[PDB]
Length: 84
Ligand SMILES: C[C@@H](c1ccc(Cl)cc1)n1cnc(-c2ccccc2)c1-c1c(C(=O)NCCN2CCN(C3CCCCC3)CC2)[nH]c2cc(Cl)ccc12
Image 1: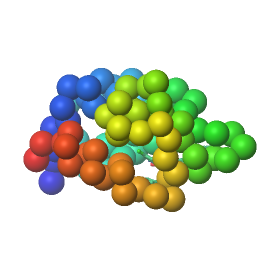
Image 2 (image 1 turned 180 degrees about the vertical axis):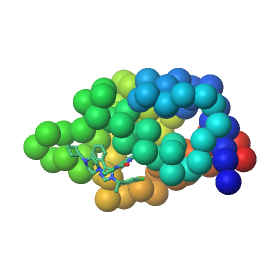
Image 3 (image 1 turned 120 degrees about the vertical axis):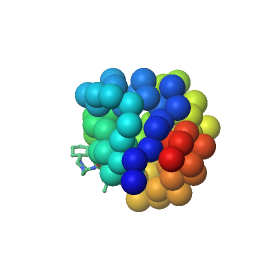
Image 4 (image 1 turned 180 degrees about the horizontal axis):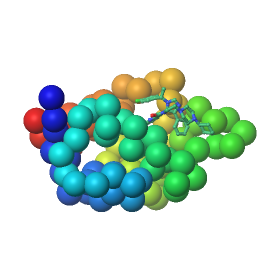
């Protein structure tokens, strides 16, 4: 049930308060949400929108932005970054 994130993703999780390097998928998603908060990547006016371009998260997603209503690009990134 646990996964090991690749190094760039691991750095992101730690910036969000995570410890160690083995996580459940739900932990990864929790900490990614927390990362978005701490780095203030969301639009205060449209809080469903995240602007990740120019942040390491954007580089990993291959995106400038995404909506939290549309999780599709997120789970594809996790496939390419989480080793089970
Ligand atoms: C349902 C869930 C979700 C979870 C996964 C996915 Cl692929 C989509 C959606 N979700 C709903 N809104 C968010 C969210 C929105 C804006 C900024 C930060 C987080 C999230 C995300 C969580 C999370 O663990 N969220 C706890 C509840 N959230 C409500 C919104 N809250 C705040 C939003 C910003 C302003 C203050 C309230 C934080 C607590 N983790 C995520 C990680 C990513 Cl890669 C993307 C989004 C989220």
